[PDB]
Structures are given as C-alpha cells and as structure tokens.
C-alpha cells in the first residue's frame, strides 16, 4: 500500500496516485515536510495521518528532526505529543 521514493511516500490505486507526502532533508540533521495531499475520495480514511507517521519513523531512524511546513502536516504535529521530541523550529 504505502510506497517510498526519493523524498516521498505515495499510494497508487490501476496505478493512479491517490496520495503523496513530500519531505526534504536540509543539513545532516533536519527535514522539511513540504506537502501532503490525499485524493478527496479518500477523505474519511486517516491516510494523511498515516503518511505523516511514515515520514516520522524514517526521520527517527536517520536521526533527523522535522519542520512541518505543510499546514496539514503542521496540524498533525500540533495534536500528536509523540512528535514533540522530533519537532524543530
Ligand atoms: Ni493500507
Ligand atoms: Ni506532487
Ligand atoms: Ni481537527
């Protein structure tokens, strides 16, 4: 279901992309979440949260903290106490 590319996690339905999140390393220690979007047809299903979660597990492994620039990503960070020890500003 959730696939990985260079600076991205995405999901494809026939192979059409119905969700993505795009993140960018700066320095050796930071990453930015620039963009997350999910097709409007999936809107109920928590897919955005799940995509943010993947970027977080990845950045935890690679010892990078995350600046959640995308408003949606930023929203997730504000709710999730678990992401406090991985946030930077
Ligand atoms: Ni799935
Ligand atoms: Ni895109
Ligand atoms: Ni809400």
Image: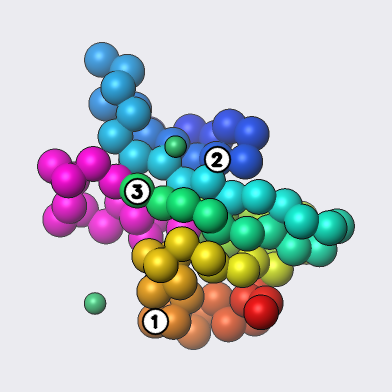
Q: Dividing the image into four equal quarters, which quarter contains ligand 2?
A: top left
Say which label, 1 or 2, has the lower sequence index.
2
Side (left or right) of 48 relative to 6: left
Local crowd size for mark 1, using a 10 Å CA cut-off: few (<14), some (14–19), many (≥20): few
Q: Is there a contact, CB below 8 Å, between mark 1 and mark 3? A: no
Distance (Cα) linking label 2 and label 3: 12 Å
Q: Is mark 1 within 8 Å of ligand 3?
A: yes
Residue of label 3: 37
The secondary element bearing badge 2 is classed as strand
The residues colored magenta run 38-52
* Among the 4 quarters of the image, the one containing residue 33: bottom right
Nearer the observer, disc 1 or disc 3? 3
The secondary element bearing badge 3 is classed as strand
Residue of label 1: 79
Q: Residue visible at 66% across and 50% down?
A: 24
Distance (Cα) linking label 1 and label 3: 18 Å
From where the camera sits, is residue 27 visible? yes
Local crowd size for mark 3, using a 10 Å CA cut-off: few (<14), some (14–19), many (≥20): some
* Among the 4 quarters of the image, the one containing residue 12: top left
Q: Position of residue 1 (x, y in %)?
A: 38, 34
Residue of label 2: 8
**Vertical arrangement, residue 41 with respect to residue 64, above or below:** above
């Amino acid at each position: 279901e959730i696939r990985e590319g260079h600076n991205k996690f995405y999901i494809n339905d026939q192979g059409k992309q119905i969700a993505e999140i795009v993140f960018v390393p700066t320095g050796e220690n930071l990453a930015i979440i620039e963009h997350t979007d999910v097709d409007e047809s999936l809107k109920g299903q928590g897919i955005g949260k799940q995509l943010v979660a993947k970027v977080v597990e990845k950045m935890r492994r690679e010892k990078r903290k995350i600046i959640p620039l995308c408003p949606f990503a930023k929203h997730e960070f504000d709710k999730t106490r678990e992401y406090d020890d991985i946030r930077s500003a």
